[PDB]
Length: 290
Length: 288
Image (cartoon, rainbow over all chains, first blue to last red; front, side, top):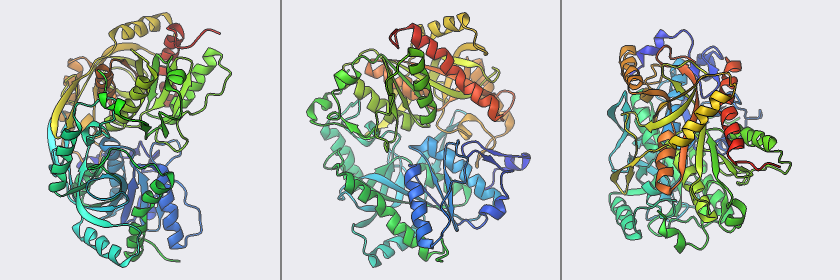
């Protein structure tokens, strides 16, 4: 389904990328894109892009395509786009609207979005990669909820189960220094109270209450929790694209709220999704290997 | 109301600032804080901190207190903290949790949070400063909704009406090149569909339907729309602090959907011109 209103526009402005439809020949510039890789940090996604450029053997430094005074960054390495989405569903939806419009104007069909994130784990050790087979909200329902013109709307979430399976199989043939698990993911709007953290500035529950909640979701098949998945996976489904989440876990919340703060091992954890995804991209014609 | 769990912890980590309760003596470093100014952008709040430091005649370094690789920046000049909140309620709630904890460990009581931002206008000309007299959701209810351990929770929003009146009176005494109006503010969770924009990647409504929704909002006293207000005002209320929004409007959505580079930057400076003078006249900065 296509937004019929876009045909009504003579020029369209990407407010959060700092460019318009007059800035490029979108079809020429982006027409070959088949993957969009995203996470919450501009520095981290820039580093993954650089890392993909190295894999592709690409000699030109990776530079921002978005305007430098704009909110979000955008990089391109061969048939892959890279962008940040900031923290949370509202920020992410802005990015989803603007990138999926870009893809539309460029004629890109059936693109795979890959969120490479960090996440809280449940019942897996820190450093585990979780491939989302399912994304649910804090009510454990597979929907993203919105309120549009004041009326409640629910949009079903969906992940690319074929891609999940391919990544699972790839991980078995790689030698990654971690475990890879297929399981469900909770998206929340609050890093603290909605994820059952006891150490916000406000907390209306006990340790037992938090544990009862998290154990129940574990036994529902949830293995991690983050803040954007609902949004990405519901949005792609409606705009005709595919989505997966590939997130490393940085704490086992069934045991603690605190991340064992080895500054080295957190950066270690952060690299794991890219190692797996980079190879998937290389094996699925995301890049030219120079 | 205090979070009792905090006293159980030995070292508490501010994940999004990149420091801990061990990094500093919080009472000595932050104990004099009575104001926290926030907006969406690190660059924008940085430049406002430098402007306040200039206004105060503070010659000392105004460096980022947060870790250079942390999610948010944090600056201080005299009795004011400065930090960015990103876009949207969830990002802003993280900032609100970590800053209000910081104030808690520092012994700061009854602090005024001030959001300086941009916003969609309803029936006011672009460049208008709206001082929020209430913050509501897209159903026009003065609450921020959460789902905590799977249970719906509704947290009332509140603004510091007295501070709103003082800014209004100050605007009448200053010569700012804008109008200043007191009126209501919608917080939404989506820049496009939830604010009735027709040019998202998805849209299930007509121009007439979004106009009816916005006209209704206006009829109920709403004069602008943005994406964080519900979060700041509900949170300050529960933690014993006060909050206000001072937002310039950059488009009149009742007339047009489209907001050039020149005039927008001029718009952005306007909340800072009014607030900076308010802070100068209400003991935010010492007279030196």
